[PDB]
Amino acid sequence: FSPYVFNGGTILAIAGEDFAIVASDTRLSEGFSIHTRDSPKCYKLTDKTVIGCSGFHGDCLTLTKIIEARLKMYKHSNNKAMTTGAIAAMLSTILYSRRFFPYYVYNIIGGLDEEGKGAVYSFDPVGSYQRDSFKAGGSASAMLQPLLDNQVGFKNMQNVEHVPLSLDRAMRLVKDVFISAAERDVYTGDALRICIVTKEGIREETVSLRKD
Amino acid sequence: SIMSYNGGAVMAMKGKNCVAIAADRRFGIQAQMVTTDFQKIFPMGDRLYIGLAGLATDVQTVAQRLKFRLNLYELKEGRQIKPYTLMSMVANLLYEKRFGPYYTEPVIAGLDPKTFKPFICSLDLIGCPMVTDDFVVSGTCAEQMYGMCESLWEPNMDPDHLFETISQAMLNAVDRDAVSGMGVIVHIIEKDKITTRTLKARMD
Amino acid sequence: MEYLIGIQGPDYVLVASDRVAASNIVQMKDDHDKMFKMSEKILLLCVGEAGDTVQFAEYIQKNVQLYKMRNGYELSPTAAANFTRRNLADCLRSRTPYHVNLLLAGYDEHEGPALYYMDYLAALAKAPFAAHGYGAFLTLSILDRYYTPTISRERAVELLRKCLEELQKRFILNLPTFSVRIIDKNGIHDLDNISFP
Amino acid sequence: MEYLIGIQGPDYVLVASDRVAASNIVQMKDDHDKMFKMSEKILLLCVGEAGDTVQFAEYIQKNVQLYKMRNGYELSPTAAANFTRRNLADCLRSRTPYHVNLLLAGYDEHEGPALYYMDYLAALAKAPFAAHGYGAFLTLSILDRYYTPTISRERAVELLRKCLEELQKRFILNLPTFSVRIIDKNGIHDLDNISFP
Amino acid sequence: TTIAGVVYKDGIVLGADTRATEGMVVADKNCSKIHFISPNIYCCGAGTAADTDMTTQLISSNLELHSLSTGRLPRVVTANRMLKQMLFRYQGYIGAALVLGGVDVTGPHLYSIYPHGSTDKLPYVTMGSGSLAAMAVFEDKFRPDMEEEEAKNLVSEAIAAGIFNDLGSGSNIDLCVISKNKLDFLRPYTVPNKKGTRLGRYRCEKGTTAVLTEKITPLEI
Amino acid sequence: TTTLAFKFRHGVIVAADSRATAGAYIASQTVKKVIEINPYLLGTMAGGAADCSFWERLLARQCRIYELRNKERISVAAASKLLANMVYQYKGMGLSMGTMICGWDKRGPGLYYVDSEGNRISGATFSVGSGSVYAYGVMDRGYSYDLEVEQAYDLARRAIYQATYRDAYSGGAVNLYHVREDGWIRVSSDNVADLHEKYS
Amino acid sequence: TQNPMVTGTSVLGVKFEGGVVIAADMLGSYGSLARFRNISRIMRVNNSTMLGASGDYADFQYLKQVLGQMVIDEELLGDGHSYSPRAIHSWLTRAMYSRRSKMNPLWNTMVIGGYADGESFLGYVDMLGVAYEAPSLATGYGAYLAQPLLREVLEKQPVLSQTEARDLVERCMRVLYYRDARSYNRFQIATVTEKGVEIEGPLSTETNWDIAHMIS
Amino acid sequence: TTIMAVQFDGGVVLGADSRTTTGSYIANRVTDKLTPIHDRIFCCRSGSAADTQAVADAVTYQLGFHSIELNEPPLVHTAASLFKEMCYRYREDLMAGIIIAGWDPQEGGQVYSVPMGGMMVRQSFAIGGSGSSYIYGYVDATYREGMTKEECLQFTANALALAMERDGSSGGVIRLAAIAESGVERQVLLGDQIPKFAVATL
Amino acid sequence: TTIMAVQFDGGVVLGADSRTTTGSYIANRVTDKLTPIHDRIFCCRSGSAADTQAVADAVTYQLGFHSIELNEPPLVHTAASLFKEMCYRYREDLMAGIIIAGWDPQEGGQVYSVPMGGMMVRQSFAIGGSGSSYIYGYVDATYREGMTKEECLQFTANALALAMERDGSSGGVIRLAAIAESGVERQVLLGDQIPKFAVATL
Ligand SMILES: *C(=O)[C@]1([C@@H](O)[C@@H]2C=CCCC2)NC(=O)[C@@H]2CCO[C@@]21C
Ligand SMILES: *C(=O)[C@]1([C@@H](O)[C@@H]2C=CCCC2)NC(=O)[C@@H]2CCO[C@@]21C
Ligand SMILES: *C(=O)[C@]1([C@@H](O)[C@@H]2C=CCCC2)NC(=O)[C@@H]2CCO[C@@]21C
Ligand SMILES: *C(=O)[C@]1([C@@H](O)[C@@H]2C=CCCC2)NC(=O)[C@@H]2CCO[C@@]21C
């Protein structure tokens, strides 16, 4: 009896000066079959924080419920909503509590810090986390990450101006990168769910990917 | 995995009347680097090249046996080999060892010796040929190369833009693989010249 | 574990090996030679599994000398190295594989000095410097730090001494004495052994 | 592998240990102490698995010193040895066994000098001389050949030097320096380290 | 992989997908899984790509030799015997699963050949990882003695079912129609999937890449 | 991973790389392998990232509690002993930690090596990780107790650079720290590409 | 349980305008042996919720015991609050995940169907705690043989009638009888609408064996 | 799989199911497990589809050659002997349970069983396969001496239907063959031709 | 082992073989596999002798206590429920296949099957054990509705004899029990009382 299974899915987060973007694919699969074509992997935590979970789906559901409960408890005890960094540290301790029977979940947190700037935090299944500027996770993370290193980080580029990232360019880049991923990865496709975090709140967009 | 023992990445890309083939330069035993000038691209003709990725011993073995067979073919036939014929020859060589496989995957890039039409193909562990009109990759960082190539490749590129595209793809892909890197070498094959370039890369 | 090292200079090659033959926990021999003379300007240094080392090395030696007898001239270092790699690779997939790690040093009148590295899987590399063993892990960075392509043989012997001193300080095995040879246009010269009291 | 040795004389005990702390192939430390002071006239020498050695040794040390504080006099070497064997044996069949090999040296005003040998299975033996490690295999016969019960401490230091010299000649591990202590009616005395350049 | 085949009133329809994968990554998007055996016999291959390729090439050469010797049109039973004897000889270590369709003097014949050397002669067959999805369509909608267009639509539907419901199948749909009077090798027949349009131009400009050494060799024409 | 530390006349030098790997995939090139336990006490991380982070953060909490209760800062030996006792309880369960604890206390400079196996050793020079063997050679050929501060900086940078050159699982940047009597300072973060330019 | 003993094959579910329909065969297999040929694998949970299970029949019976008691306990209170299909689905997910985390799974795959507040519910739970919602569902071999046909109909026509849904279920059951070795010719059909839960008993499929004469 | 053969005065009756399984998936649902080895000699194949097909083809080849050289109709015992030799020689490599039934002018109608392992025994009736286990008591209770061809056909159909009801590896249609001096007659029973037995209901 | 129970209007009939085996050696050849759980409730035990004995003793204890507290004759369903609870709770530890047959004033004669794993199903007839496999077709062909007690006894004896002929783990004597409102009647069939079926001979 194996307590795990791989359910696929790709998530992406890009931090801006005044925005954050969290995107995911909506396909849920097991083995060579497709369970559903309409399962998003992004969840709203606060009005300033979104989380992205990929991996084993039962662990994803349980962890989502646990995080929501902990946020409610914190608001009861401390009379304020939790910040993005506090959520990241709490999630790190939650993940390490299962060190000897882990959560098979890959997590990316995206939101705004206390100065209003974009913040992305990436986790491994046991709770090691880091603050980044962009990050990809899931089955097509190895395809997506080099392109973001080139196009957002300007790595290996010679005499190229480091113009700050705009929300328009970031949205176009996300759409293009997921279009490229759905070509080569069998676990990625169906639809793309994009969540944009700004001081005005969270805004959602859906675009179509290829169904084969 | 026995393929990942030495690492290595090879890539071939198609242009307008031109082909490009790029490879990494590291030779190492698992985690230790031994040399930084290991040859993985071999000439099989004036406008025909083969790149091999995988176990370095099989890389050298396959290159030498392939040159044996190609030299005999060109002596008997009095002609230069076409890229598709070389693909078939390599597939035959690899499938003769079906149950004792050579641990190498080849890419072939060339121009037809008469009509000067670009050709690129890839072969897997036992010799199933894959002919493409865009690009082919092989090695330990294949997924990274796939992402870069899908994002950057455009049809009907001139030699300079082809060089820029393949160089960016290889550099950014090997920067994310631990056992690949330590330099990149690129060959641009045209009708009238071969251009070989070494790239400024990360040596960590 | 046994240790081999080779440094290439503008007109010379410098090789050193350890002189220990061990069984279990005892050192049975402390003046063992691990260098085989292929020709007047070629040396083969072999470590690895017992029996495999001498059998493979002496087979290669016999065939190289037979080439000299049959043709009236000697194999070049590159040709000898490729012959060695062919034989090791051919025997790799058979029922009698050799578990040997090798260095090949030589001087060619037309090509100059050459040092070649070969692992037990029969991959052949050409290097300015190289080493074999667990001590390689400790001394390769010392070579990286202080090696220049234009180095004289006095400075090469000094750098070799640095590497062996590091082995005496940080390595867990008792490797107290080392055999040192040099190959130049005049042939193979035995230098003094490097010993640590 | 680590090395311990003990020689008992008419009025003294002589103990020596090696000073090497190793991880994989590198010597991380070369001035490590493997001798623990139980009381004014008792020494414990412990080798074995990492962590187990210090935890067990310091537990024993703490309880022996607590006996001194509570009762106003000190445990005799025999009683300390039996306490140690009881604790190791009790933990042998539990879920947290200690993999430690021990020597215990002491002087009693009424019973004289004593040397005790204990293996990881918690069997306790009393010996005139004893050793622990892979080097024991090489040096126990030297002790058998030259030891007499009436030996003076100068001759004991000479015999210890013979054993360590044999380790330098025949042993495959690099054990270059040794800590030497003596226990007599006046207590514990640190002798000079025995070093081999 | 999804491969399928039906018999209709005048002959054979074979269908396949065009995706080739190495694990869970897509290696080829335009693979041809319908192989030529003789001008009247064709084969759809699944399993290990190299095994399928080499086996079909060997049997095609042997059948060409036989037809040159006899001067007559080859028969599908001859191909069936050759293939299954070869596959039984290797005890299932040649991983070829084949759908064999032909028209000879005795009529339309369709076979399913399994890697261990087992053969079934049937009026409709499916093989591959998407075989069950195609077989559902066949068991729902198959009728004996169909017309050419009905059979083409049915095989297209079965291949599409494999494409959209299996992770190892995708891309385009290839068809082969074999009657006694004609052969139609339709690549591609339908395109159900395309790549979305790109929204950004990833600055491709000269001088972005830094070069250490350069060597130019002129070639003579 | 390559971590390095040595004691010299003017204090303690700590240096680390910044590459995080998951198999042969480079997860990160900007990871932080030095934890700041308190303004006078530093720790390094090698092995399991999560293990090292969690347990050294736990050590930081315990050390703060010590300072509150005893109204005096903790010593390096006591902190290393606390960490060793904490990780001994989980022996055989699969913890991967290799740590250096560095600081300045009433006995002067201090440097301790603590690993999940159970070792706790004092010393003057240490290196932990995959590339530690390559760093040891350069450090041993260059190390003196009477080094000048800039010379010590250069030696540490050179050793980490050579380790990243030879080891596949080391790379990124060299992060350097100097423990002095008044506390530690962040010296530099130098990319190994720039160091390749400087040294070649 | 670590080894299932008596099992059931596949369960089917489709939602339509005004309710949900679920289908399952009446067979319990002991390996390859069709041992218990008259068992019901569909359960009426409450007036809005019905449940069907595949896998270990003993685990299914345990779940039926626990769920029935929970429903009775809620009805004793008399406060006008009932369990929705969604709440029963969430409770089932929690139960399965808790059992999996103790390394003592319940060897079942479950389909939950319901109709509450003018809205249809169809939900899937697996042995490991994977749970989701979809407009059509099939477990076991039906995931390979039946889900294609149901999905193809639903992509073209996203809203179905009761007649169309029942016809589609009967077609899929026929396909399962053709191609599944652990299948049986008698099945039950449960429907949930605004009137509640109705179970229609031993139904059979009409088979066609004409291709038997095409073998030659 | 369920295969059966019954001997009557002047011939034999063979019967089989029509299911091929790859695990729990039915690859072929109308398969023919009755093979003509010669004009009046048939085999029922159980076990590995590939192995049984190969053995049957080899025996057909050898028996045809033998019959041409001797200029006689072959004996059923000879075919059973060829099967036994091949199945015993390659018993480590083959999974093949065979029933050989036929008519010859010298001994009449004959039924031989070659189980796995390569033994050969002549029986008055023989059953084989995975479903054969469920009908052992029924055939022992119902078999009587001196049955006619029609009674043998009914008996075989009843037994095969009972086996197909209880076995997950057996099912489909019933294929029957009657072999006598006048020749071979083949039947298919499908749908409502298959005998029905009432299921217990509470 | 072969155990059987058949329901008739007004009661039940149970039957079993009498073989205990430790491998291929018969340790007990006259064992009683029919156990009185209560006055009108019996169980047939299959599987592990020790496990089935322990479970039967525990259920007898619990049912007696329950009947004393309620001052009523127990129900057959209650006994089947107690067996099901124990067999499901300890399904990892126990190898026990049970048949529970009985009569109660409310529902009449009842037969319940508790297979391994701990499921509970009411049947009109139930068979179990290792020999039960060989008589599945026979019971499906021979069972008819509205049998009398004597016909049920004959049917059970025939089935058990057929099972004992083909199974190496079943044999000995046949033990039968008829349970009705008037009580329990027990029989042993041995030697020539056991039904005989002719063996095919060439
Ligand atoms: C199909 O079966 C498939 C293809 O590679 C296919 C094989 C034979 C002809 C060439 C291409 N075989 C495979 O191994 C993968 C796994 C699932 O389907 C494949 C794409
Ligand atoms: C280093 O040991 C290493 C780092 O990923 C790890 C991560 C950051 C902080 C602690 C050190 N651990 C590993 O497992 C890989 C393989 C070897 O080196 C790593 C890069
Ligand atoms: C029967 O034994 C069976 C058949 O597939 C096979 C079909 C062709 C003729 C020989 C018999 N063999 C098997 O492996 C499966 C499993 C059980 O029965 C089969 C259906
Ligand atoms: C029957 O199943 C059997 C009996 O020994 C046992 C005897 C007492 C009552 C319970 C049943 N159990 C066994 O393990 C052997 C092997 C097969 O059948 C047995 C005889």
Image (cartoon, coloured by chain):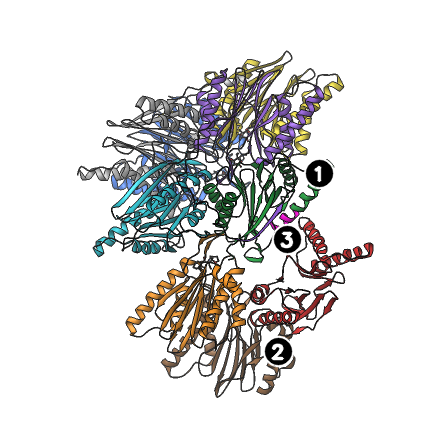
Chain colours: A cyan, B green, C red, D brown, E purple, F orange, H yellow, I blue
Of C26 and G206, nearer the camera is C26
Residues packed near mark 3 inside 10 Å, few (<14), some (14 to 19) or many (20 plus): many
Residue A167 in percent (x, y) is at 33, 45
Is residue B53 found inside the magenta-colored segment of the image?
Answer: yes
Local SS, label 2? helix
What residue is pinned by disc 3?
C121
Gap in angstroms between the C-alphas marked 3 and 2: 43 Å
Mark 1 and mark 2 residues within 8 Å of each other at the beta carbon: no
Identify the residue under disc 2: D163
Q: Chain of mark 1?
A: B
- Marks 1 and 2, how far apart at CA: 71 Å
Q: Position of residue C63 (x, y in %)?
A: 77, 55
Foreground: disc 3 or disc 2 = 3
Nearest the camera: A174 or G22? A174
Q: Which residues are magenta?
A: B51-62
Question: Is A4 one of the magenta-colored residues?
Answer: no
Q: Chain of mark 3?
A: C
Q: Amino acid at mark 3?
A: Leu
- Say which amino acid is labelled 2: Cys
Tally the marks: 3
The answer to whether tags 1 and 2 share a subunit is no
**Residue under pointer 1:** B73
The residue sitting at 48% across, 23% down in the picture is E155
Q: Does residue E72 appear to the left or right of I58 in the view shown?
A: right
